[PDB]
Amino acid sequence: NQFVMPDLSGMFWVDAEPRLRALGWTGMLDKGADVDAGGSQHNRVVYQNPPAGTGVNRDGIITLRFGQ
Ligand SMILES: [Zn+2]
Ligand SMILES: [Zn+2]
Ligand SMILES: [Zn+2]
Ligand SMILES: [Zn+2]
Ligand SMILES: [Zn+2]
Ligand SMILES: [Zn+2]
Ligand SMILES: [Zn+2]
């Protein structure tokens, strides 16, 4: 908890990461398993950890699962 986690749902990774990095996030990305979530969700953020509203550390680990 040094910056509040945003809701990244629906973003492409080309937009998801720079948004996090701009918040000061210097931590490591854990890219999780893809999620088959239909065509509209293809390569968009489906899950995230920590959830939005959670205080995450500047170098804490963030996990993303993208639409298959
Ligand atoms: Zn863009
Ligand atoms: Zn990167
Ligand atoms: Zn992938
Ligand atoms: Zn499918
Ligand atoms: Zn489809
Ligand atoms: Zn797909
Ligand atoms: Zn993908």
Image (tube, helix red, strand yellow):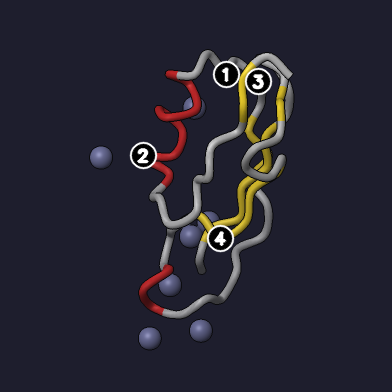
Q: Which residue is mark 3?
A: 27
Which of the two residues, 57 or 53, is positioned nearer the viewer here?
53
Residue 42's quadrant in the figure?
bottom left
Q: Amino acid at mark 2?
A: Asp
Q: Count up the numbered dots.
A: 4
Identify the mark nearer the N-term, 3 or 4. Answer: 3
Distance of mark 2 from mark 3, alpha carbons?
17 Å
Q: Amino acid at mark 4?
A: Val
Q: Which residue is mark 2?
A: 15
Q: Position of residue 15 (x, y in %)?
A: 36, 39
Q: Position of residue 65 (x, y in %)?
A: 61, 55
Q: Which residue is mark 4?
A: 46
Q: Is mark 2 within 8 Å of ligand 1?
A: yes
Q: Check disc 2 and report its element: helix, strand or loop.
A: helix
Distance of mark 2 from mark 4, alpha carbons?
14 Å
Q: Is residue 2 left or right of residue 26?
A: right
Q: Which residue is mark 1?
A: 25
